[PDB]
Image (tube, coloured by chain):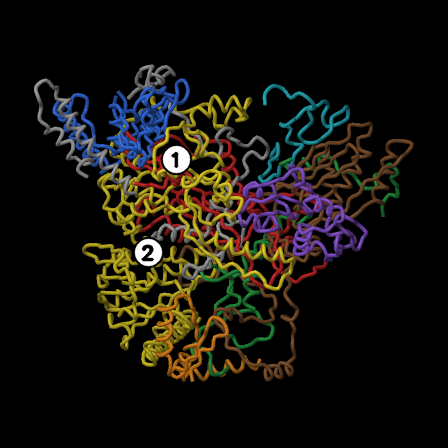
Chain colours: A cyan, B purple, C orange, D brown, E red, F green, G blue, H yellow
Amino acid sequence: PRGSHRGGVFPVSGLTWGMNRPYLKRGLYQHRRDHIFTPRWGTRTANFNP
Amino acid sequence: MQRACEMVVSLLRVDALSQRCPFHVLNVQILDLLQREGLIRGFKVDGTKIDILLKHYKGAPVIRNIRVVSKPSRDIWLTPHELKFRTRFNTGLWIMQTSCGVISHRDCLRMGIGGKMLMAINNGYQHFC
Amino acid sequence: XXXXXXXXXXXXXXXXXXXXXXXXXXXXXXXXXXXXXXXXXXXXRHLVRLGXXXXXXXXXXXXXXXXXXXXX
Amino acid sequence: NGRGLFGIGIAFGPSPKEARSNAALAAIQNLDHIDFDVGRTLTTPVHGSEYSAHVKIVPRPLGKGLKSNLRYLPLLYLMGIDNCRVSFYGPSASARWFTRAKALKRALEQLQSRRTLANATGQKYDLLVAPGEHWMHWPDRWFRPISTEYARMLERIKKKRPPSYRRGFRAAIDEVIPEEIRPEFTPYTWKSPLQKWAEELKRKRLTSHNVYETEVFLHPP
Amino acid sequence: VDFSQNRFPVLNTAENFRYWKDRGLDRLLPRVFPLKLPAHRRVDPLLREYIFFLHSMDPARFSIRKLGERYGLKERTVELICREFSVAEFLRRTELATPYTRRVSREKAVLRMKEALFSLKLGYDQLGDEDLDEQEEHEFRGFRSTQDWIQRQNIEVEMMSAFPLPAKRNPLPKRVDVDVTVHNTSKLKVMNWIDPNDKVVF
Amino acid sequence: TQYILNQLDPGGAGRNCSGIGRPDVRLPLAKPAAPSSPDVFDPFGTPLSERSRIKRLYNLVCEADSWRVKNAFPFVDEKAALVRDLPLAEILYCRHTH
Amino acid sequence: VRHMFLPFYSKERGPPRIRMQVAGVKGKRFYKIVAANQRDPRDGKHMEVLGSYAPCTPSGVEELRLRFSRIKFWLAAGAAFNSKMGGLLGNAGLVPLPPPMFGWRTKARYTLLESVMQKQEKLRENQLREYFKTAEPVVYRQVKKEERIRKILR
Amino acid sequence: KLRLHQERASRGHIEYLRQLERPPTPSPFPLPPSPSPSSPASAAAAKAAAFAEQAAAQTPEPSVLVRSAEEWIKRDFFFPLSHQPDTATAGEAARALERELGLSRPQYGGLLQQIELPGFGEINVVHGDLLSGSLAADAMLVPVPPNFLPYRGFGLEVLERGGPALQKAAFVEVKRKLQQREVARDLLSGQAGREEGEGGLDPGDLLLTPTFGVCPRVSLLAFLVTPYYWQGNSTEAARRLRFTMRRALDDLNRQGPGSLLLPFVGIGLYGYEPRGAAEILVESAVEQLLQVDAVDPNYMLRKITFVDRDATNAALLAEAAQAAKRAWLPEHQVVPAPVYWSQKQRRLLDVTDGMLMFCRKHTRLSFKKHHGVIRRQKTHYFSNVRPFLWRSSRVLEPPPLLLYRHSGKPADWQLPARPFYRQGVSGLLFPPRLRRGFPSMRVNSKGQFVGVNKMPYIAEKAQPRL
Amino acid sequence: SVSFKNRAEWRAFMRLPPKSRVEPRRPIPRIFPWRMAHNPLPRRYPLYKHRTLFLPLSLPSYSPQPAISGVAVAPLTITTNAAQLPRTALLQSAVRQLRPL
Amino acid sequence: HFLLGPAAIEQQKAAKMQRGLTPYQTELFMWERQMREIRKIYRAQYLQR
């Protein structure tokens, strides 16, 4: 395929779009990985160390 | 061939213990194949008619569908490697007529012989012509 | 005597006196009609008897333990 | 329920929300059982028709899962089908789902199972990843326990048969009770020094009392 | 405990085929599964260095097969260990790059992170846990493993009888062309194109 | 007995089994008996070797962990759903292949 | 011509020959070794595909694929070929080695060059053994100041 | 022995044919029942079909060129397809070529392989019978279970042939070993108490006894305690055998015998894999003959002969010995040709700091910057794929050529061919009949092969795709 | 010794010797018989999960296979991978290469 | 073996010259003489197979 998507563009996460929805407009939003399951198999640190 | 396409109707009856169909040697052979495959309880030959005693299971009949392939106005033949593709991934019975008799598509596939596709029993939704 | 009764995969029974004859017949069968597998309860207990005779000192303890386990 | 119970309900209401609630109630009342196979594969492709509405269900190889329009993938998960692709060609008349529902119901009514086919026919319908799953039955005459006196009587009455090593070997088992073992760290002469060292360390770690101790912090307070 | 019409208590059943695999609405639960890591990255680096030393010293007495046999690894794993260690040692001793300046792919960087966290959690293995020659075990290994591709069928429909049935037609191996090198020098490579169907061979 | 044992844990020449049915392997019987009348036995010590685990069952047991899953203010909800709801996001969140 | 191979001979086009058709795309060119008639178009009509020849390949070594039995068959049938094909077949071993451009007798300077090159190769092998006796991956050598030198052995 | 490129190409062709050949396996066809479970016409058709299918299974088929298209079509629709198509086998031409090359040109083969370590000894691999075949040796090694009461196999056969005398001698030796072990255990317990102030033989245990007229080729029988294969993993099952062979050979060498006859240890009763066991056996023999471990060598064992009665097992042992030659003997060491030539031209370079300026980049990681999604599929196929397809068959890169390390000439043993199958399917139920068995030829009305002029069909080999 | 202070010097060093514009100069690209035209690659999260090559073995023969020496040889599963061949399959492949023909 | 070994090149080198021919041609003609032989050898083997 080539060119922009011609037709209906839906988020790949499956979340609806609207005024009070996770997405304001139509789109794929493939970079938004917070809307897909990414297990945390590592560690975590804090902004400050008292 | 006409008699077999007619017997399809008698085989597809529901809420019936037995049903009659026209007589023919081809019908008798197809009935033999069906009984060997355990799709009918039995059948009886009475002159111009054959009385098929049908089989049921949990209310519904064992024969859930019949798809006619070879009609008297059009033959359908297949090579072994076309029969394999056409019967791919299906538990239904495709009746084949060959120089070795009226057999199942599985017998035809093991024998690698060219055959004429007559009927498909309980083949779901799988046809090409 | 020696009887090679063949219920399935013909087998034979040896008495430690016909072992030579059994071996000869097995070799002859393997040479003439291959793949006719023949198995005989030849010399398991035959070796066991001589082992017990050699280990008579500890064979008594072994037999006592076996009897105790069987009774249990 | 995603396992073989599915239904569709059509209902009216003063508002869309109450209409949906009544429709859900009707669907709950209309639930029926779908004839699936425990192997999770279709035995044949399936088609359903209602006027100009057409529903098609095509098998897929075991492992691919469900394929359909994302608009109706949740419907597939509710139906509980697996390893198949579902396509709607639908009516072009005034209605869209009123008759498509009947078409889908008639399609689902076509599905059968290997157990159903085998019971109806008397023949073998064996899934290659599970042969003999449905027809193989070990007779109860194999597992008939006997008392000691009757065992003596049976040993007396019966005629002995020589034990065949090929078919008789590996038969020294009896009633078993649970016992914990750990033969992964049992020292042997043939085990190399490094293997012994690693196995010893592993067994100490596994049997240690500090296991099951979940500490989120690497450097504890 | 549910019902079964026939007695066959084994693990080779459609119910137990993919045991523990979701079969209902739980298929939508976001479960976390263990991450897979290479054996050549699971074994301890000191064991890697020891294997590399043995192989680079005496590849005959310390064969790949023998090293794998002693340390519970596969021949491919031993080969990978030796290659990686030789590359790292070459870079370090020639002072070309440190272990943290060799440009690598994103996948290999993620693999390095995976092994780092694996060691921090469980610690490097002190011995290999693989098998030298894998066994014929009935396991699900993808959708391709669940069907007979040659027969193009997932279900073997057959009749019930107490007597022998006609044998199934066996497949014949495909006769495909191959290239076999016959003469290679620093300038020219000559290989014979073979057609296995050609009857007259000379 | 051997047939059932082989079905439960395949083994034989060239195979790695648990040796459970072997006459020379120890089992945790409830009623102890002769390992395997008095005439035939093992005159030497020859302790029975241990039995190794069943690999399939052990793997199932180990992998079960991945599938393990971890008055009131009387206010009644009237704008509630009887059968919940199954949006597309619930599927596409975790089932990546879709 | 023996009766068997008569069809291989064309009244309109000529006798059979073993030759090469251009193949590939502009820039990336290799050759398909075929048996055709003399007056056939080079990239057109032919009778059989006998192999391929790629002088430029990523591996840096000219690649020659041939059906050995078929080349033997066509030589027996009588297909003709030119100097380049004869040389390729000689290198492949299918036919005796054709003489070089000016003949074997005329090559003495080149034999002297080959001998000198072999002697220099042996000298470098001896130097490499002397290096192996120490095998220092990194060295420092003077310009003013000492610079680092890496002794890579490719 | 082959020194011609043509001969070696024929050798490779023969090897690939070996790969692809499958011998016929006729099977009985069930007799049709003669009570009729169907109509009489169906029964007659069944009888005819059964006989026809048996004939089709048991008869082969010639090539296409023998018959015409209409005859083949009529046969295809009238008879069951034969199980042995012409394309199935290799051919009399290939068989004759193999015979001429010597690859495949009165019961036992004899000496199949021999490794000669000058100054150290010899390891022979022989197809022969140890017992009935009993050109000389000192000790014959016999594997036995730890309990020393075999129920079937070579050990039981040897004990039976020896009779009560050999059985008693072996049992006496076992009793002595057990008593020594018990004494050592008691001493160990006493010494443990002093510092504070199992059972049965193990793998590698050796017992030497007189032959009692069992094997006249030897004068000593060394019973060796060997492991089993079932325990644990295959790595463990083979570590056991390696340890056992090391101990057994070392102990026999210390005992003194200079000649040893060894069967295939591990196979048979103990359920080992012959292919994996042969490598261990041969490598252990080589290492012991070389005395790799010893700091004070004890060169006593100098002839080790692996004797086997099965052709397959003897051939596997010969293959293991060939691999051992490749590994150990510098003459037989082989190397890929690219590596050989590169190292032959090997040179020492002087790389400075300024020569690596552009060998390093700004980015820490590398990834593909463009997806591989083709915008126009047919245009891509026509422009960038089809022009380079000079044949429609799918062939992989050839395995590298192995050259002898010392000389550089091609090795007599080369890697097997690497065929490709689409989606991994390597079989066809109904392979099409091909004319390319005799390419560019036909059969004239006289009955003779003649040439054919015809433009080749570029897609002939991709129909069906393989 | 040569110092490549800029990219021009690096290009000069790396440049191949001049060749005529009538001969084949660019190598013909490799074509793998399983991805002739597309080169799939992953384009969807997770981007770096482990992918294992599986080539089906199915059932090369459907008739009773006698044991080779002592190993069963007869198939027991349909899930065998042809890129991870088991012990007995490798044994069969080795015996075939040793058959006398 | 003779034709494809190192003897053919030596025979070419030893071929005698005739007045009017360059050194290459006299080797080419001997070289072609060996070619007519190998062509006949291939025909015999192919025909027997």
Q: Nearer the viewer, residue H113 or H92?
A: H92
Q: Label 1 crowding class (10 Å Cα cut-off): few <14, some 14-19, many 20+?
A: some
Rendered position, H442 above or below E77: above
> Which mark is first along the chain, 2 or 1?
2
Q: Quadrant of the N terminus of chain E?
A: bottom right
In percent of width and height, residue H164 lies at 34, 81
Residue H311, visible in the rendered structure: yes
Residue E34, visible in the rendered structure: no
Rendered position, D92 above or below F61: above
Specify the quadrant of the image occupied by residue H210.
bottom left
Looking at the rendered structure, the number of numbered marks drawn on it comes to: 2
Report the chain holding disc 1. H
Q: Label 2 crowding class (10 Å Cα cut-off): few <14, some 14-19, many 20+?
A: many
In percent of width and height, residue E109 lies at 50, 34
Q: Quadrant of the C terminus of chain E?
A: top left
Report the chain holding disc 2. H
SS label for mark 2: helix
Q: CA distance from mark 1 to mark 2?
A: 30 Å
Residue located 63% across and 28% down the image? A30
Q: Residue at label 2?
A: H315
Q: Nearer the viewer, residue B101 or B93?
A: B101
Q: Nearer the viewer, residue E162 or H188?
A: E162
Instruction: Check disc 2 and give the amino acid type.
Output: Ala
Instruction: Check disc 1 and give the amino acid type.
Output: Glu
As drawn, the label of residue E127 is none
Residue located 61% across and 66% down the image? D178
In percent of width and height, residue H240 lies at 40, 61
Q: Residue at label 1?
A: H397
